[PDB]
Length: 106
Length: 106
Length: 106
Length: 106
Ligand code: HEM
Ligand code: HEM
Ligand code: HEM
Ligand code: HEM
Ligand SMILES: [Zn+2]
Ligand SMILES: [Zn+2]
Ligand SMILES: [Zn+2]
Ligand SMILES: [Zn+2]
Image (spheres, rainbow over the protein chains, first blue to last red):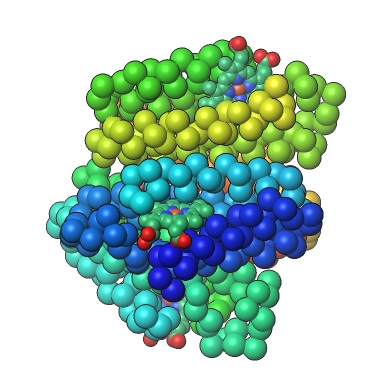
């Protein structure tokens, strides 16, 4: 999938997590986000098209995906443990990673 | 790319890191490993064809890529710091992750 | 050190990172934060004095320190790479961990 | 506790996990390992007594504790999920971290 599709998948499922009542819902949404974030890894954002594929900027771009992937990973464990509220809070917290990357690169 | 290509990329660059003489070579190889691992995320292994895409087995399979991706991430920081030997050591230690997944799923 | 002293160390160095001009200042402050957070691990917060040392609650409390330690770890790599701004951003972002734990346990 | 005691704690509980029959035994063991690892953070190893407390070598020493702590953290989540065998395998795998640090610093 393209960057925009992966971004909408990320966006859609974050809201699913907010409105969710149960672990399964959170679980499912986080799984989809993990796949979206991993697939986003190879993308070149439009503001970085003029940069070398292995530039410092591109390195920093992809680092944000590492952070987001790590966070989804942990939130998923929480939801697997049945810690719904705390997985939802981890989801709220990862928005900081979404925002930080958007502020620099979007 | 498919699973097999990602796996060759992973294997090829691990050997490149072993033979490397400077941090640029390690850095370049780890970057290629991270892309390969991230791209591998969505793959279904032949041994798990018969399992649901959202099965416990498939979750455990993808978990190994989380572990791999985290370790590459960290090793790349070490290489960026010019810590060639310790980045090469981190790379040798990664093999545990490679092996553990192969033993169960390959 | 006590929980309070570790908490002040954490507080003080966070501000040091905000005002910092170079990577060495940030590195030094994160190093101090890492030791404070690791030393905090064994503490029982006043709100949880009545809970068993290996209770659900106490596990969740210490989980927040795993999260914080992980974040400092990564931020320190960024500072080591000379990525001052992004290390400072990483430091602003880990405030979410600080606050999440306080909201629940302070 | 001192370095030796923390190392004994780490060693004893690793064996407990190997012999374990259920998730509770592995959970309990990993919990103790986490505390021992976090307490070990501040220690100076006999081989690095002559180095500055904020030396490059001391930084690399403590870095291995970060990686150990992260692995215990993850292994604990697996045990929490009731994935006993997988938690026991994550425990086997972190021996790589134990050994890597001993090779350089013990
Ligand atoms: C879970 C957190 C995230 C959420 C909820 C999210 C969601 C979104 C949304 C709704 C958009 C609007 C455009 C669209 O429809 O795709 C977008 C765009 C974008 N995001 Fe994110 N995103 C997240 C994480 C990230 C991260 C970590 C990065 C960078 C490493 C990033 C980089 C971008 C870029 C470059 C665009 C513009 C794409 C384009 O216009 O071609 N996002 N994202
Ligand atoms: C740096 C670590 C790794 C290395 C060097 C590595 C290396 C390889 C190599 C050389 C192959 C054979 C190439 C081929 O398939 O034609 C392979 C296959 C495979 N690997 Fe890995 N691998 C690594 C990590 C992983 C991880 C973490 C997993 C699972 C989480 C995994 C799962 C698999 C699977 C399922 C196959 C079979 C694909 C097929 O033959 O169709 N590998 N790997
Ligand atoms: C870098 C992030 C953090 C900062 C800057 C911070 C800061 C503080 C400060 C300034 C205090 C007041 C203590 C005093 O006045 O001496 C405090 C107390 C406290 N903090 Fe944190 N904290 C952080 C992270 C955490 C985390 C991760 C946890 C738990 C997982 C936590 C749990 C507590 C508790 C239980 C208290 C109350 C102890 C008391 O009664 O004094 N904090 N913190
Ligand atoms: C879970 C993995 C680990 C296990 C099972 C383990 C086990 C041990 C054992 C059995 C000893 C013998 C010392 C004694 O009993 O007096 C020891 C010592 C030591 N270990 Fe580890 N350890 C682990 C992790 C680590 C790590 C990650 C580091 C480095 C950061 C490390 C550094 C050392 C050092 C420096 C000593 C020497 C202690 C002294 O002589 O005062 N160990 N460890
Ligand atoms: Zn966790
Ligand atoms: Zn590291
Ligand atoms: Zn990083
Ligand atoms: Zn995990």
